[PDB]
Amino acid sequence: PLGSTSDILHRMVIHVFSLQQMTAHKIYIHSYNTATIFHELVYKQTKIISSNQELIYEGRRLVLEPGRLAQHFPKTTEENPIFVVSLER
Image 1 (cartoon, helix red, strand yellow):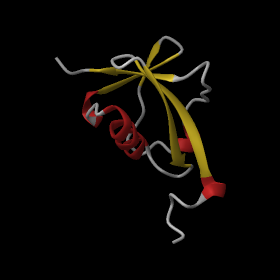
Image 2 (cartoon, helix red, strand yellow):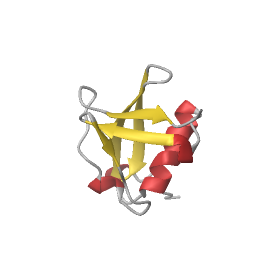
Image 3 (tube, helix red, strand yellow):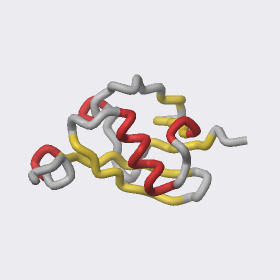
Image 4 (cartoon, one colour):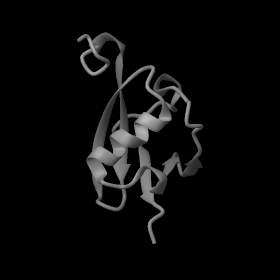
């Protein structure tokens, strides 16, 4: 209150596809949340532990520094999402 989850005008969406579950996910996130928070939000929907999440964008591994702001992620759409792969095993 306001709180970053209710801060609609500063929120954005990142489109993710989990290959392990074969499920699409919309990651609504504050523009100023970090990659660390992004992974937490992905975990909430996929149960893939943050440090087990490998990200792929346009067929290449995507490496994001922990502090990278959501607003500075690559642009995604439902047709061009960030794929998530698990390092587990």
